[PDB]
Length: 72
Length: 72
Image (cartoon, rainbow over all chains, first blue to last red; front, side, top):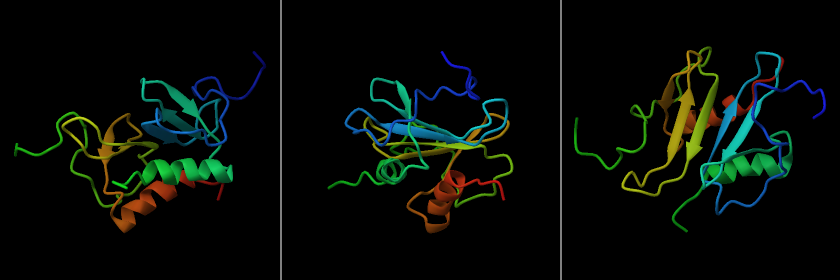
């Protein structure tokens, strides 16, 4: 465990746009307390959560794609 | 209370992009059970939640703007 500026937050280690199938939702929150960092947790299908890098391009997709999800 | 196809979900009545200041985060989930509808809950600063219409244009902003939040 390294001394980073993010304790309150739950982010794993911001993945770079993983694959969904399990990923059923995501949460995005602004900074504030000592974590003073954004929030981008994708809730897994099993009811878990992961964080991804919205600053990342592929990951910025993760938001948009999670937002899409049409009938196909 | 009308008989709609969304009980499981918590959505208030999907607002059309309200103003933040309180809105500190949001959650987006896919359909599945009898709710069989998306999910777009903006968690309020007081720790509350609201739903908005991501299909809506202004509201699709609510996602992108909530995603932005820079130093300014």
